[PDB]
Image (cartoon, rainbow over all chains, first blue to last red; front, top):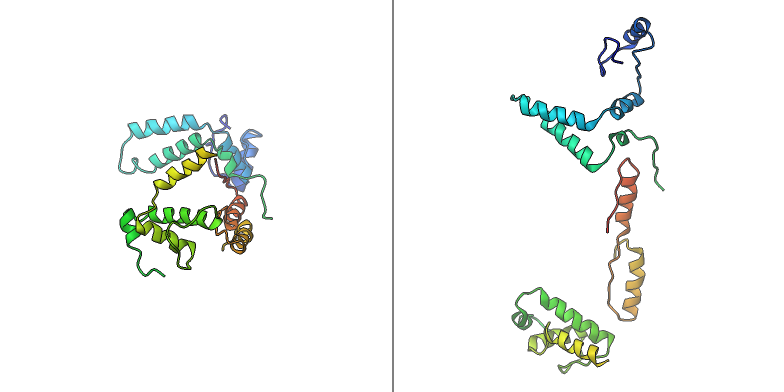
Length: 98
Length: 74
Length: 48
């Protein structure tokens, strides 16, 4: 929901979500389940985020900016290079033992 | 039986190939088709093979030669 | 002497025939490990 004045990934409690839906109407969609996280991660292009993180690391340099960002880039590189789609982290079907 | 295995070690030196050579000799000795070149004293195949490698009459080389010998003689 | 089900019988036969030959095969506990790992959301397999 970009039309409404709300962040893409922000907390909106029950009363808050109620009043937001009452005011903005059926535009600021929200979910409260694991499927919410699944939708958040599936509709997210990894190459663009990787380029943005690389640009941020190259441009902005600080004691705290040097860390907490390179590991994110490494995780993104591992995900794209391994080919494992991150939606596979949230499992749908569950195996059981013989 | 043998108390110390040193003559075979000196004949080999690497200390790792001697076990392989003696094992590959003993396997063919026990399966049959060959005769002990050293006179036996009522002992198992492994001791006979190790005494043979200690005597300096068998190694990792002449086995290949004799094996190619019967392989081409077929 | 391990969980190799297809090895204990064959070693027994090699002894009684005096063969004294061993083929390793694969321990069954490794298959147990593979099966229990695949019980969770983690693929695992052995290539060639």
